Amino acid sequence: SKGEELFTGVVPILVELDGDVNGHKFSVSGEGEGDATYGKLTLKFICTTGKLPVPWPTLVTTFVQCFSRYPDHMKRHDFFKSAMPEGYVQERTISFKDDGNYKTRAEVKFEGDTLVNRIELKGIDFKEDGNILGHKLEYNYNSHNVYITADKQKNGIKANFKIRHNIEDGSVQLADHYQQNTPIGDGPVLLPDNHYLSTQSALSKDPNEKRDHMVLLEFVTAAGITH
Image 1 (cartoon, helix red, strand yellow):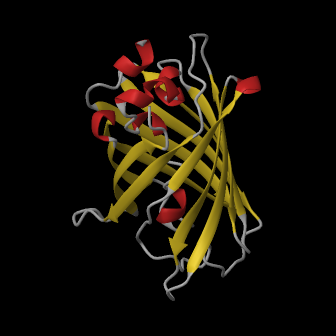
Image 2 (image 1 turned 180 degrees about the horizontal axis):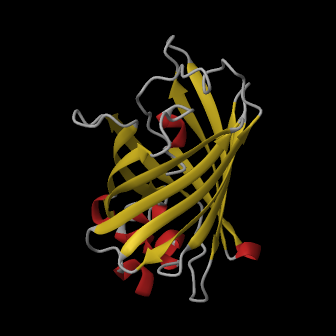
């Protein structure tokens, strides 16, 4: 297919986010590359407005599931690549248990040969010294399953999953995710059978970087369908 063939090699990625969480405004720019053949993402993000007013881990899911590895036998279930190059809208509500919520709107599409994720994020209802605004989350990231279902009336998909953020006291901050994606263009897109994406992510720092930043290495494989 046209969209799947755009991902057989390494593809440059740009991420641009503007956010407002409880009136804290901020922006993030990211750069890196994806290799969907291996489900692989490598990026570096920089807060361009100074200090990031929320913990970096809370933004990982917001910061390109077209780079997930779909096994060959699951090609007919890969909505994300099928929407390319014209792209898709991705919307979420992220509910931090017993704290505030993010609502995100993003568009993911090619600009030339570069895959771009442009995001607007709005956060409300956060506790001033909760785990988010109080920066109580560990700088690490767990492994999840992202459950995908077709959303036929939208010519798209939905996803529902549970992100676990470790808290510095050893506890866990749940972030419930609900997601809907809608294609932008007029080519045919794939409406999948139920399946999920198996994720893992590693967060690190660049030792030469004194801006507030995050280095991310992530691997994602589609699963849950056998034939």
